[PDB]
Length: 11
Length: 11
Ligand SMILES: [Ca+2]
Ligand SMILES: [Ca+2]
Ligand SMILES: [Ca+2]
Ligand SMILES: [Cl-]
Ligand SMILES: [Cl-]
Ligand SMILES: [Cl-]
Image 1 (spheres, chains in turn cyan, brown):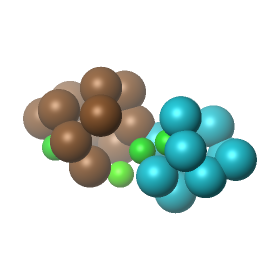
Image 2: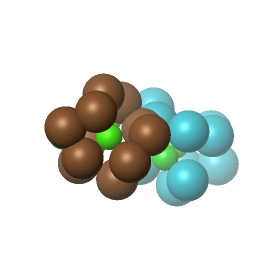
Image 3: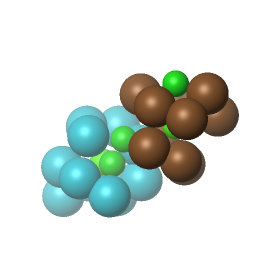
Image 4: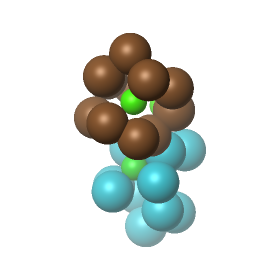
């Protein structure tokens, strides 16, 4: 995952 | 997104 927001959301 | 499977999941 990317974004530091977990799966999906921000890449 | 990527993967044709919805937000997140498969890239
Ligand atoms: Ca994310
Ligand atoms: Ca997405
Ligand atoms: Ca996906
Ligand atoms: Cl992500
Ligand atoms: Cl993502
Ligand atoms: Cl996709």
